[PDB]
Length: 156
Length: 190
Image 1 (tube, helix red, strand yellow):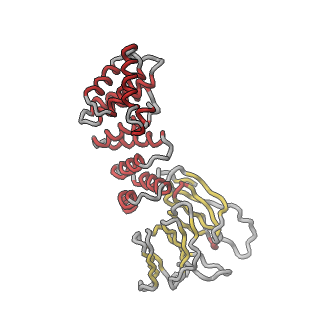
Image 2 (cartoon, rainbow over the protein chains, first blue to last red; image 1 turned 135 degrees about the horizontal axis):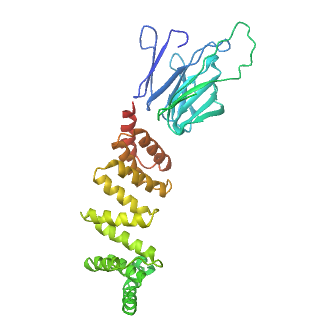
Image 3 (cartoon, rainbow over the protein chains, first blue to last red; image 1 turned 45 degrees about the vertical axis):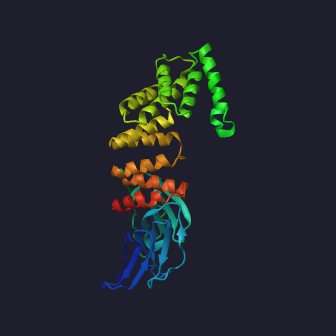
């Protein structure tokens, strides 16, 4: 977690475990499908609360609280997700997986664009972090992504 | 043909077609559709020696541009008659001839892939099965399962997972393909 206090792990047996820095069973969730991609929402002055976003292999992305109670979103997907990455300040969400496409979403779940179609599974996609100065003025329209495909291509 | 494929509706149409075909052969023996229909009827009527004999005498004829298609069909039938027994070499010969004279046959490449898979040559069998699946565009299920199994046995788990996902999306009544190859590939991926 971005607060440095919590830790979240997933198992292909369907178990999602949330622990503290002392590695104790703070929360356990049992599913029926393997767990591949997990992330923690970045801290934000507007939100200031951290939730765990996990992409299951039953064509769904789920939001989980600290206590383990689901937020009830359970957004459905056409394709099985593989990787989930959160942009800085928690504004965007880069989702990859089946159909060989790298897509962008809002944190709510609204589709915006797709980035690329690599004709093969994209194992890992990452976003470029940005640093803003004290009172800096800039549109910051530019965005950078790095993709890795299964064939062996590392594209930007 | 209609009498043969009409089933037990009349039970006398097939024999009348047999007499008509025999009379046609008496008047004109070199008519390829006539011999093909009589061979099909012999297949229907449990006859063993006569059907293979007719197929053989049809094989001797040189390729005529007017009656190619029927010839191909007969060749395919002969190939099937060769694949029903251990004589795989002659089946492969007929299959190679058919693929030499045609590049869009559906059952031919499926039979070739089955032979290659049974001879544990998985790369060529997978290629032939993939080409056959491409020919009949994403509708058949059995050859899809065969391709998934071949990919799983060849350590190509990504393609097997894709094929299993597609076939499960198409036909949800196939639980056999879910616990056999999809799970094994999923667990062997990482």
